[PDB]
Length: 17
Image (cartoon, rainbow, N blue to C red; front, side, top):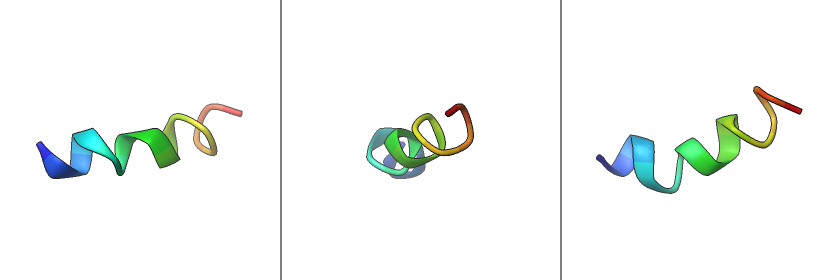
């Protein structure tokens, strides 16, 4: 869940624009 918790906030900002 950790990778989908805080780390998800990175890919949703960058890998989503």
